[PDB]
Every structure is written in structure tokens, then in C-alpha cells.
Image (tube, coloured by chain):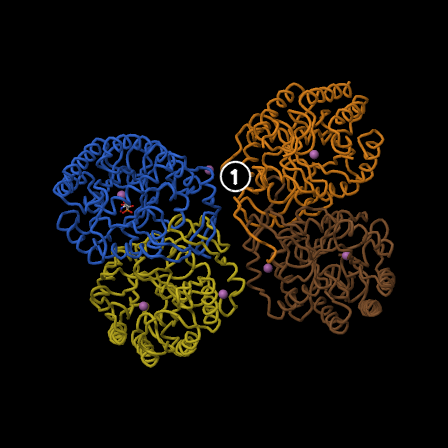
Chain colours: A brown, B orange, C blue, D yellow
Amino acid sequence: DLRIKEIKELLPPVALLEKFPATENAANTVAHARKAIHKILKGNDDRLLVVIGPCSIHDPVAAKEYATRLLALREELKDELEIVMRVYFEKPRTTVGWKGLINDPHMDNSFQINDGLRIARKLLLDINDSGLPAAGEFLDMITPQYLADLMSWGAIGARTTESQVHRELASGLSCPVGFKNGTDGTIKVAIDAINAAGAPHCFLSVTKWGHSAIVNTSGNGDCHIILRGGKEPNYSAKHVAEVKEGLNKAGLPAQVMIDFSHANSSKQFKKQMDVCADVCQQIAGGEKAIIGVMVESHLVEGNQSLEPLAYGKSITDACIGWEDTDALLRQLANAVKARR
Amino acid sequence: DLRIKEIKELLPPVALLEKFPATENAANTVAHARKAIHKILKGNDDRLLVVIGPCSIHDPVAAKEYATRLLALREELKDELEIVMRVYFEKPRTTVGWKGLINDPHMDNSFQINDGLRIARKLLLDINDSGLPAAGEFLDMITPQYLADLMSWGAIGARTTESQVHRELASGLSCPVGFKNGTDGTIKVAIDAINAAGAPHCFLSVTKWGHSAIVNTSGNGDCHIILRGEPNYSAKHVAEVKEGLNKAGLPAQVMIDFSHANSSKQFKKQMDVCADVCQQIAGGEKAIIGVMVESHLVEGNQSLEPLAYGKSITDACIGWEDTDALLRQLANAVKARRG
Amino acid sequence: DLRIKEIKELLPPVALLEKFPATENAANTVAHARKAIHKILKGNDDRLLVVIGPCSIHDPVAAKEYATRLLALREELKDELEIVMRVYFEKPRTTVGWKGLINDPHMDNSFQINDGLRIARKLLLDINDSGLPAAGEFLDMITPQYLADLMSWGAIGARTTESQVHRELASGLSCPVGFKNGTDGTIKVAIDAINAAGAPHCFLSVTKWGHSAIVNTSGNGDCHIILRGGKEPNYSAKHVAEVKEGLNKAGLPAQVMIDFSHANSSKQFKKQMDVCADVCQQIAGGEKAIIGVMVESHLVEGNQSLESGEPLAYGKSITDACIGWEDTDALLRQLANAVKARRG
Amino acid sequence: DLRIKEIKELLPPVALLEKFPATENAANTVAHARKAIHKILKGNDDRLLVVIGPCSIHDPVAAKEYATRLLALREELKDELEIVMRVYFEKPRTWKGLINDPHMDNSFQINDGLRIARKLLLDINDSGLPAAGEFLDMITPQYLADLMSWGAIGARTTESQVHRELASGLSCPVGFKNGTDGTIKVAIDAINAAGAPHCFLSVTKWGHSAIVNTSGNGDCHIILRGGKEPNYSAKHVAEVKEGLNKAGLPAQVMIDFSHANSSKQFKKQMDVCADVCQQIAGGEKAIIGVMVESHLVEGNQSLLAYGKSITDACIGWEDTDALLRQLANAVKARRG
Ligand SMILES: O=C(O)/C(C[C@@H](O)[C@H](O)[C@H](O)COP(=O)(O)O)=N/O
Ligand SMILES: [Pr+3]
Ligand SMILES: [Pr+3]
Ligand SMILES: [Pr+3]
Ligand SMILES: [Pr+3]
Ligand SMILES: [Pr+3]
Ligand SMILES: [Pr+3]
Ligand SMILES: [Pr+3]
Ligand SMILES: [Pr+3]
């Protein structure tokens, strides 16, 4: 009505799925990575899930370069690390800001969202087709139909871990999903989310044809917590123990994924290397509860603001550079061989 | 989609708008109320916005009797109060329970949402058509298209004040919106939410036709905080909130939720909160621009065999006699603050 | 799309069905009438189906006045006639012209089709709720979803009996369907259509949600020919016998509905009474194959034109000329008398 | 809905458009061919439109082989003939085609048939061979009409208001067949109705019903296909020309060599060719086009052999080369 200025046409998921179908290789990649993460979340596999990549995708060419480098390390460190690339097309803002490649691919408030979906699905498809699994945050309620079939692992953001519609979304997603602890370090909201997402739900959603409908979900038991800090970090064994106690109390597996960035690094990118030190000591000491980690990495460390932009630098959160990334990864895989 | 078991047809919004179109009376009710709340939020009216009514509606018949009683008080106290009926269809919770009138109108877990939507719109239509404005809660992104044209005020869920998708929704709502503070009593997320909601946004949404589309909003400047709690209705807390709002550059105004934490989960304590808030107002507090009270015909609650008439099946409410006294307490207070 | 000037929002059928649901009595009218026509078609009832009423609906008020009068005769004559009102909202044109109430309800080329659908369904609902069944021509491929649940009988026009998409539509309609012979008098196109409509089909159509979809139909066994004349009228006994033998050779029951109007009256509205006199003699003489008739009838006889700009007369056709109410009463009593004589 | 058994999902047009967008080559083929046919119909080109190809496409491989052979004769005889391939994906009966049942088994895999048909049309146009189609359905056109340079309304639907409405909004020129009996009145009526603007309900590229308004289509003409007796002779053209002139329309005609004009015999198409060539070479400027049922192999088959029709019987490639050259020489003599 009065506060809706304009309404514009939107391609339906089925149109993106027809233009950019999954290649056989892409399908195989997704299936294998999901099965491997299920094996890790059920304890049958001792390796570590590493979700690593840019805070946000804004340049498909650099992403293709990053993916080529990360894919090499995935094949080399595969005995200790299940590497999944961060391919974030959606970004939650504390108040306002650039919301990601889908919402605004030209970074200029043009909102060419149909091109955003075309660009994002094609990049996601090419990455998977090369053999590299991909991960994203599921923030929007309507975009998942265009992308989810190419997602090997998903995240629910700290500012939406408490959101019913997002817990419902998780309960129907074909991939494992991680829920961030609240902005204040509150762990309870995430356990409740894991519990909710493991149950069936009945709710309103949008179909592959772009039409609203009633949807019934089965429940997703491949769900786990992601520690991302609060006013202070929470990546330490002590914190891990507290969390593992809350998980056992709730009838849930005492498994944790540790995010080296955001509140766990105080928004200082280089601090991810020190969080890595601490977590690697926990693994080498015997912590089987750390089943995964998450790292904000890019070709060039730091971040830049939004006219032409520097190559390989994040336009959102500051990331560690590739050299630090190659090193961080070997450290993690060294700690995994020690724990084994 | 291997964790999606079934997909069933949903009536498009235009089907419910064609079946239950707004009468001229209902449309006038909504327009007048929205204007009145804007005037209060702009500091151009010294009257108190009162959103009052059941925790959740589970019986349209009892809701219409409530609306008749409340309408009478709305006319008697209009010089001091802008009375809006709380027409909430669900109690958001994580534990198991009735999913509300839209999700489960027959209260049996049959999830007859088409039926629920029909019942909800018809009730909203009837209440507005009688002259009583209605206030709702926005818990998802798809049902507002069926109902918001009959809402004069809305509240975003407490568990979603932080969510970008709910802030995007508020940016394009035609009615004023209240954002609840944090479970710790902090006001930062609600300030972030008011800022975000006041900005223009572009996002994906379902249209009146039942199809996803791209929508651009203007931003909603009629948003405010709701203080809902340990309790935070006290004058110290109100001063603290006013300070945070002034520093953030927002108007130092607040709506106070008398129920839940602010009442330590004891329905009768809403009368204690009322006594305190009335004290703050009569002494001169102009920041308190609204209140929220959980009220029904019959006080208390019951668990969902027949049910007691007019008694909440969700959270406990004050009953009509207390409601009549509370509203007179608030009105006498508005007279005092004035002169 | 260089020749598509404008595209506009259309209410989906679920909106009209939700706004105007069938009442209990309306649904009863439709179900009873369809069953009664099925019975006549199977040879288990000796009554005459009579489809009668305006060439086109353009005024809901006159249409309801007409319906009330017709309903009273429907009740009075129901041992002899199964009376169904023509409630035609769609008109096929020889070239160009007003396409009917749905396409253009204000009759001024404003094409307010959403209001037309609303006006049309509400009228169909009021007429059925009163107890009077309704008949229409199925011309448009999208409008049936808005109306077909309130239709007891349908016609596929002379210009579309040959059309594959209309034969497909008929194969999935829940009501009996009449196929008019071709505009040049050809019977075979009508027999082919009956056989086509009796078979299952798979085709593209629009659902009640206004979306395209793939539909599978079961086939419609309640189809028959309508005799509407060609270069010359084809209502006489010589013509009915050729149609009877033509139908049997194709393996179909020798049954016919005769349209008294259009080419069988040589487009001279009062000649419907001359056809009536001949068809009555045939029926009362023992002709069982004549299972129905069709008559263009209004409150006031004649027609009038919209081209004038003059205010329209009440109760008078803006399309084909029609007989007025007095002749209509006399004609229905003639038919009932003949059906009684056929029996005794 | 007692007589409706099942309702199955259908890809919206936007899905097939996104999967199979028009190459710039395809788009240019379409545009140039449409503008050239306009020029023939406005009488500013003495060239002859030739719509030629199989009665029906059942094998995309054989259809692409035909397209290749025909493109050669197209560029060779371009100064006399505007050659457009007949790519007929919907068939009228009383098997509805590759779109309705691509695998030919009553499996009715229409989403696959739509995918196959749009791909074949896109490939043929990308090559430089414009395509011609029959418009039988009101929904299929939104998935294929962008790749069509000319279209026909079948004889069984010339009289139908809903097909005239569709014709009035098509971006391509349209031919209307005379009805089964040699009479042109329904076809003259159809040309007049399709020339006028119309408002009607249709399905958009998004798969939703909506109200559309059309401008009218002035690029419509008659197609003589005969009836009980053939109507391609000079006497017949003259009668049709007088009828057209009385109705107020350009006195122009396309002549279908097959069907009744051939009395259901594929070799008689060569005889009609003889006759029409004699008429054109004698100075008949009113014959602006012809239609021939041609395949790589001659004849037909039922319920397969390669490059042979499973519908109407067609002429083989040798006869096809000969006929195209005959028409070209005839148009050369008309010009000279
Ligand atoms: O209603 C019927 O049963 C019909 C349709 C008939 O009413 C037609 O619509 C006009 O006679 C055409 O009028 P024009 O020839 O002026 O376009 N039978 O043919
Ligand atoms: Pr980040
Ligand atoms: Pr674009
Ligand atoms: Pr409550
Ligand atoms: Pr129901
Ligand atoms: Pr008529
Ligand atoms: Pr209107
Ligand atoms: Pr053929
Ligand atoms: Pr397939």
C-alpha cells in the first residue's frame, strides 16, 4: 500500500533451475559432501569440517580463483579436513548496508536481483562442478529454492537463530545446517533452534514455481551449534565444556563448530590465527567435540569499503589472506592427525 | 527436497480480499486509527495509545463480545485514550502447543490454514466494521498480505526484532510498528530495528496474487520501542530508555507492555504495573506514549472437551472488571499529565 | 510482443469461487438438472430438455426478472419439460462486435473483465439459488473455471465445433454438452466432435489458481448434436432422419436437440414459433429422437443496437432478436402439450 | 471436476526462454524474415514466400538435416524466393505431435516436448533458416512464437473467435486456410477480425492467466488448400481475388500444394507446382506465397524409417530441389 513504492517481476526458481541445471559432477559433489558431514556429525568420521572462504561473494572471477586454490588444499588435506568453500550471497546487516550479491549484484542500489540470481547460481554451479562443495547462510525465505540444491552445508545467522521461520526453513533443507549462538553469546537460543529444526513443521513458504503454499517438513537431525562469540570470545576449552554440558542436558550431541571470526576474533582478522592456535591445541589435546571450524578467508587480507574496487579484498568483514589460509589449514590438519 | 514431505494449496490473498473486502466503515476505522497513532508518535497528541485484548484469539464469538464492551469504553475515554483491540492469533513459543487460530483454527492440529485465514480476516473485518481498531502481531512474511489492510498497529515478535527479514517487512507496513526490547532489557537491537525499518528496502516477497516478486519499500517512520522487561516499566528504566533513544537520535518515546516479565508472569500484576505507569504519567511523563495489556472477558487461563467461555487458552489475562478499572486508571492519569 | 499493447491483472478463479460459493440450493439445482439431462440422454426419461432465454445477458436485473417468470413455468410444466435458462455470457462474432457481459460488461469497450466475472458469477449463483438451472456457451478457454460449477448444460457454438481445443474442453466438463452443426449445415463435424469429446485427452489448460498446467480428462459421454440450420433450416423430419441415421452409423444414439433460432428461423425471430409448430407435430406424432430444443427468448421481443448511443430499452436483446414473454409462455405450453401427446 | 483425472505441473514459458534464449543470429533471422514477408504482403517485393518442410516434426535429427539442405537452396534462390522451413510441432486431428507426445507413446511428456521443440526451433533459426508454424493451442505459442517468422491457423479453427484473437496479437504474419469446401468467406472474415484490436484472457510468459489487449494484425492473408475440389487454378484465384477486393482486402493468396489441392496424393504437388508456375510466369502478382509438404524421403509411415513422415505424405528431396527451382524461374519470368 502506501509504503510499497514499486513491485517488479521475479524469475521463478524453476527458471533458474532450467537455465543452470546441476551437472552430474556438481550433483556428485553435493551428495558426497553432505554424506561426509553426516558421517562427521554422527561421530563415525574423525576428520574436521572446515567452512572457509570470503565473508561475502561480490566478484565471481576472484571466487573462481579462490575456489581453484582451495580445491587443491581439499584434495591434499582430505585425510584430516573436509573443506567446504564459503559462498555467501546474502549478508545480514546490523542496521543497513549492502545485503549481498543476489540483492544488489552491481553494488549500486540497482537491485538487479534477477541478474543477481543468475550470476549467483552460475558461480555456485561452476564451483560445485569443479568438485568443491559450497556453503552459505540461509537468510532470505525465498532465495533458498534457487540455490539450495547446490548447497552442501548451511548456516543460520546469529541474528536469526531465534527466528521461527528460519528454524522452519532449516527443518526442510536437504543439507546439514549450523546455528550461530546469539549476538550476546547466549547458547540457549541455538539449542532450542537445533531442537526445533529437528522436528517436523507445517508453515507457509514459496514453491519452485514462485507460488505461495503450505509446506510440511520432516525435520533435520544434521544440525549443530556454531560458537561465534558475544561481548567476549567463547572458543576456549572452558567455553567449549560449558556448551558441551548444555548440549548433553538438552538430549543433543555434544558437538561444536568454532567460528574463528566475528566476536570470537574481536572483528580483527589477524586474531583468527590465534583462535586457530587455541582450537588446534584443543584438537591435539583430544577434543572430539570440535567437529568443524569456520574461517573468513580471501585472496587478499583485510577489507575495503564501497568506485572501482581492489582485487581479492572483501567489501564486508575483513578476511585472512591466502598465505595465512594455506598455513591455517595445515595447522588444523596437523592437529587432527595428532588427535587421531 | 527430501525433507519436504508434502506441499498443499494456499488461497491467494486476493481470494480472501475478494471474499472479505473492507466495508467503508472498516476502512475508515483503520485510516483514522493509523492517523491518530502517527499524531501521538509525532508528539502532536497528549493521548495514550492503549493496545488491549486477549493474549490470543481462539474463539471469534467471545472476541466480538469483547470488542463490543471495549468499543463502549473507547467512546467513553477517547478524549484521553486511543483504544485499539489486540487481535493476536497465536502465542509464539518453542515448547509444544496450539499453533494459533490461523495455523490451527479447529484446535486439533489439523493445520487448516485456509480456514484459519478466512476466520481471522472475517473477525478483523467485523471488529473494524463496528468502529473498533485492531492491532496485530507479525510473525511471518506471508500472512500479513491477508490481514494488514485491517491493522491499525502492529508488533514485531520479540524473537525477531534482530532479523533483517522482519525489519524489511516493517519498512513496508502501512501501519505503525512496535519493536520489543531484548530479553536482557537492552534496547540496542530495538534501536537497530527502528533505524533499519525507517530505511527504504528492496527484497523478495509474496504479492496479493500469491506469487513471489521484488518489492521496494519507502521506510516506516512510525516505529517505536515496546518495553516488556526483571521489570523495566519503572521510572528509572524509562529515563534510561529515553537517554538511549535521544543519544541514538530517535524520539525518546516508549510503549510499556504490562504483561509477562513486566508483570512477573502473574496476570493480576498488570494492575500493579498500571498503578506505577499511571504514577509516572500523572506526574508529567510524556515519553510513555502507549501501553499493552493482556485482557479478556474472563480472567486467567485454561488448558486446551469443552472450554470455559471467554477465558484464554494461552497466557493468563485480566478479566473485564479489572479491564474496566485499568482503562479508567489510565484515562484519569492522562487528564492529570495535561493540567 | 509488438502486437500486445497491454497486459493486466486478472482475478484467479479461486477468488470468484471464494467470493461467490454455491449455496446448498444452488448446488442442488445444478446436480439435479445435470442428472435429469443425463437421464433423457440415456433414454430413461421421456421429457424434453428446453434451453430457453436471451441470446445474450447484458442486464442482471432483466435477467432475474426473466428467470422468475421462467422458473414458474419450469415448476408448472416439469412433468413434461426440463427447463433450463440460457444464461450466455460469451458471444462469438462473425467478424467483430460486443463479445458479451464478461468481456465488456459496460458495453462501451472498456473491457472491465474482472467486474464482468464478478457480475456473471453472482447472476449465475442467484439464478441457480432460486431453483432454475442455467446453460451457457463455452467459447473462452479460461472463463469456464469461474462458472462451470454453476452450469447444468453447455453448448459449443457452430464456429467452434470443429476446434480441437473446444472438443478437449468438453471432454473434461462436468455437465452435458451440445455440439451445433457447422455454419454451412454440415452434420459430420458435430458427430466427430461428440466422439472426440467422449474420449480422454491430455492438454494445456488453466487451473483454478490461474496458472497453466497439464490436464488429463476422462471423456464426456453426455454429448449430443444441436441442429441449428445451415444455408437452409434443418429442423424438418427429412433432416432429423438423416441425422438419426448419420449418428447410428457412427455408433451414437439417434438423439437431437433442435435450435429454433439462428439459421433454422432464417434469423427471423418470430419464425421460432413456426419451427415450434413443426417440431411439436413431430414430437406429438411419435418422434422420440428429439430430446431437446433451444429458443431465443426475452421479456420484450425484438432487438436493439448499442451503436446508437441511445439509452437501451429494458428487457430487450442487444444481440440476436428474440421472442417476447407472451410468445414464450405460449411456446412452452405448446412443447409441454406435445411431450404429453408423445407419451400417450 | 468429475471428468478431470489429473493436473500435472507445466514449466512456465520464462523457464524455456531462460534455458533456450534466442541467439542474436536466431533473433536476426526471425526479424529479417518477418520484415521480408511484410514487404511481399504490402506488394513492395516481387519475391515469393515459400513455406516448405515436413507435415510434422517427429525426429529433431532428420529435421536438422532437412534444415541444412533447405538453407542451401534458400541462399541460392534468395533473389526469387523467401524460403521458410515448415516446423510444425502441433497437429490438428478429428498423435497431436512432438510437443504433446514427443516419445510417441501416449506418455504425453509435454515439458520434454516443449524443451525439444524450442531447442530445434532455436537451432534452425541460429543457422539462418526462418521457421513457420501452425498455431493450434492458446498456451504453446508463448514458448515458441519468438522463433517463428510466419504462422498458420488451421482450417478447422479459421472460424474460431479464440484463434482470430490469438492471430490479432501475434508478432508474425499469419495465414488463414479456406474452410473444408473451397469457400473463402470464413477466411476473409478471419482476416478482418484478426486485423482489429482485441481484448481477451490469455496466459503470460510467467504461466499465469491475465487480460491482454492486442493491436490487430494487418499481416494476414488467405491460404488456398481446397475442399471437395482443388482451388489452385487461375479461375479459382480470380474468384478469390474478386472476393477479397469486394471485402476490401489486398487481392493476394498463398496456395497450398498439398491436402485437397493434391487430393491427398504427394506427387500431385508437382502438378500444382506446374500450374502455379504457369500462372506466376504469366504475370500473376496475386500469388505471394506457396506451401509444400516436403521431407528428405518421400511417402509416409504409421505408428521407423529415417527422414520419412509419420503424418501426411510428403515429396522427397529431389522433387523438392526441382520444385524450388521451378518456382524461382517462374518468379524470374514474372519479373521479366
Ligand atoms: O447463442 C447461440 O446459441 C449462438 C451464438 C449467436 O448468438 C452468435 O453469437 C450471433 O448470432 C453472432 O452475431 P454476428 O453474426 O453479428 O457476429 N448460436 O449461434
Ligand atoms: Pr563475516
Ligand atoms: Pr539483466
Ligand atoms: Pr502473551
Ligand atoms: Pr474447510
Ligand atoms: Pr443468438
Ligand atoms: Pr471494479
Ligand atoms: Pr499436412
Ligand atoms: Pr524428462
Q: How many marks?
A: 1
Mark 1 sits near ligand 5, with its Cβ under 8 Å away: no
State which quadrant residue D230 falls in: bottom left
Residue A5 visible in the picture: yes
Percent across and percent down for residue A279 are 85, 61
Which sits in the foreground, C281 or A117?
C281
Task: Specify the quadrant that holds the N terminus of chain A.
Answer: top right
Which sits in the foreground, B327 or C139?
B327
Q: Chain of mark 1?
A: B
Residue A305 visible in the picture: no
In this figure, which residue is indicated by the disc labeled 1? B16
Instruction: Indicate whether A264 appears above or below B278.
Output: below
Which amino acid type corresponds to the residue marked 1 in the rendered image? Leu
Instruction: Indicate whether A339 appears above or below C14.
Output: below
View extreme (front): residue:
B305
State which quadrant residue B57 falls in: top right
Which residue is painted at 55% across and 58% down in the image?
A14
Percent across and percent down for residue C286 are 13, 43
Instruction: Indicate whether A202 appears above or below D69.
Output: above
Percent across and percent down for residue C140 are 37, 49
Query: Would residue B60 appear left or right of A91 to someone viewing this image?
Result: left
Label 1: few (<14), some (14–19) or many (≥20) C-alpha neighbours in 10 Å = many
